[PDB]
Image (spheres, coloured by chain):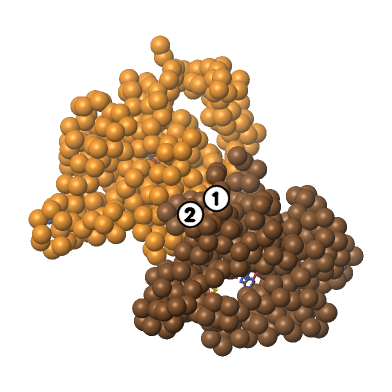
Chain colours: A orange, B brown
């Protein structure tokens, strides 16, 4: 039965020995999120926070919770130009924001830089996921800094964190719930880092939030899915495995230069982002999808 | 093709980018085993070594290889009294030793202590696997010390080592290829710790060694099977994962008292082995399968 009210439980979490009815699961989820924020000093009460929202279940749920917790949550969605997929992804995110009166920023990849993720993959040589992730992290950071946000919230859940940890162990040759802000670098927090993917999904469905069910025709996100399958196989027979795994690592145990192209932090002369888009533009000219006297002019960092 | 002779390959190891014909796989396996022994100073050339052999594919293969490498390999088999299973397991081991002129020692659990693993589990309260493993490690060590062996070789393979490592990470609340000998403690080496289970099986089949195909009605060895499934799932799509996993850990980063009952090393007053068998005898008396004036008299340690 529901541990709080004694009525019929709607959600059962063996890993925590906890069973809750719909109304108290939603409340538990929201309170536990704030418990995570407070424990790790992720946010200040009512602070402006840039929420990276893709239209999927986690970041839409995160946007909902942070709003309910009274944070000034502004969403940033990035249109990746991956066909009808990215189109629907934008619609869902827009619908969410509209029907809740939340501020939503959009960066359209194709409109800003001329190429979506598909063409970007062909032109950079990198796998689609490499160029895409690189663009996502840079743009989200850039928008945060340019719009005066101190902290960015992403919707990475426990399955995601444990998959990353697992992958690093099996494949070094191929990031913590809180990353502190530095000059040119906004802070990044993961308030959902201890919720399982199943648990975040449960919140989303019970809250009635409509998200983009379908997933990208991913390329090397097929790796994370492999890691998740392996971890969940164990989790199925041994609840709390992912939590034990991630907690165990967490509770146990470099020079940055300004990019001479855009100004943002990097370890080299020019950052991987500018280096990628330069080569993409360069190869587009040789092909020639771009005018010869065109230059990639990245938005230089304040102040 | 076979990387050594150019003829048809019989064994393909994607993880190592290596393909070999039957005759050269057998040779590669044997040479690599010696490479492991030498690298880690596991054995001295021609040294007497106690090989723990269960009749399964790994330890029978290990016994074969160590013999071929000119080591004086004496096998110790422990009869666990698990029905017809343990019976066949003993036969296979005996057959191997006979048809190769190898010295084989046998400890029959029921004959030595009065109870096989099944009854031992009911009487100790511990799961079958707990009492069984405890008995196996103690007896193998005891026989080694009592018979003047410096080093014991076990047939643990890469799948086994990586499963253990994985399990510890997911479940702390539930051991290296070489353990140095100490007073009352023989050395333990795992010369097969880098061969995958599939690779050790391949050696066994190509060498024509007959082993006990069936496995114990295991209890909590069902855990290792779960760990192996998870790891092999990744290995299937990403060769060298288990090796990367295990190597990565290995290449990165207490007071012992004499048991007042048997003399062997322990952290407490009496060791877990004596403590287990005492309680088993004690509870047998209360049941009463043993005479009241009977005492468990463990073989006290030399010198
Ligand atoms: N196109 C995008 N625009 C903005 N933010 C994004 C985008 N894609 C991902 N993010 C952020 O990055 C986080 C990780 O995304 P992802 O790699 O999709 O894992 P996920 O948990 O399966 N996706 P989601 O369910 O949407 O959070 C998401 O929670 C978002 O917060
Ligand atoms: N009954 C036994 N008697 C002697 N030695 C044993 C016995 N059981 C296990 N061992 C040793 O312990 C090692 C690990 O055994 P186990 O837990 O069965 O993993 P395994 O690799 O599946 N078995 P095997 O194929 O026989 O090595 C074996 O290689 C043997 O060397
Ligand atoms: S799946 Fe690969 S490509 Fe599709 S969005 Fe995620 S990263 Fe970019
Ligand atoms: S399976 Fe469990 S019980 Fe059967 S032998 Fe291995 S440990 Fe002892
Ligand atoms: Zn309730
Ligand atoms: Zn740059
Ligand atoms: Zn050959
Ligand atoms: Zn003892």
Residue B293: quadrant of the picture: bottom left
The residue positioned 24% from the left and 51% from the top of the image is A204
Residue B103: quadrant of the picture: bottom right
Task: Identify the element where label 2 is drawn.
Answer: loop
Nearer the observer, B243 or A71: B243
Nearer the observer, A88 or B235: B235
Disc marking residue B269? 2
Give x and y (percent) for residue B201. 69, 72
Q: Which residue is mark 1?
A: B257
Contact flag, marks 2 and 1 (Cβ < 8 Å): yes
Give x and y (percent) for residue A16. 28, 54
The chain letter for the residue carrying disc 1 is B
Give x and y (percent) for residue A235. 40, 59
The residue positioned 82% from the left and 55% from the top of the image is B44
- Residue that sits furthest to the top in the current view: A303
Q: Quadrant of the C terminus of chain A?
A: top left
**Pointer 2 and pointer 1 on the same chain:** yes
- Residue that sits furthest to the bottom in the current view: B84
């Amino acid at each position: 039965v529901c541990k709080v009210c004694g009525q019929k439980a709607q959600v059962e979490m063996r890993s925590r020995g906890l069973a809750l009815c719909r109304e108290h699961y939603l409340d538990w989820f929201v309170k536990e999120t704030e418990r995570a924020i407070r424990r790790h000093r992720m946010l200040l009460p009512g602070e402006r926070v840039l929420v990276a929202v893709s239209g999927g279940k986690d970041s839409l749920a995160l946007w909902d919770v942070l709003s309910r917790l009274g944070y000034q949550a502004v969403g940033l969605h990035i249109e990746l130009g991956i066909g009808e997929y990215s189109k629907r992804s934008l619609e869902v995110t827009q619908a969410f924001a509209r029907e809740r009166g939340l501020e939503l920023l959009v960066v359209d990849l194709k409109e800003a830089y001329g190429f979506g993720v598909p063409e970007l993959a062909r032109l950079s040589g990198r796998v689609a996921c490499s160029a895409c992730g690189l663009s996502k992290r840079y743009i989200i950071n850039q928008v945060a800094v340019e719009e005066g946000f101190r902290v960015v919230a992403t919707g990475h859940n426990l399955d995601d964190e444990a998959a990353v940890l697992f992958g690093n162990l099996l494949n070094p040759q191929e990031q913590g719930p809180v990353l502190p802000e530095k000059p040119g670098l906004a802070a990044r927090v993961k308030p959902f880092y201890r919720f399982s993917e199943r648990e975040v999904l449960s919140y989303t469905l019970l809250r009635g939030i409509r998200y983009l069910h379908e997933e990208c025709p991913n390329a090397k996100g097929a790796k994370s899915l492999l890691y998740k399958e392996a971890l969940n196989l164990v989790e199925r027979s041994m609840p709390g495995a992912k939590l034990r795994f991630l907690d165990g690592f967490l509770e146990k145990i470099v020079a940055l230069r300004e990019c001479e192209r855009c100004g943002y932090p990097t370890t080299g002369a020019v950052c991987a982002f500018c280096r990628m888009w330069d080569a993409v533009y360069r190869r587009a000219k040789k092909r020639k999808l771009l005018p010869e006297e065109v230059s990639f002019r990245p938005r230089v960092k304040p102040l």
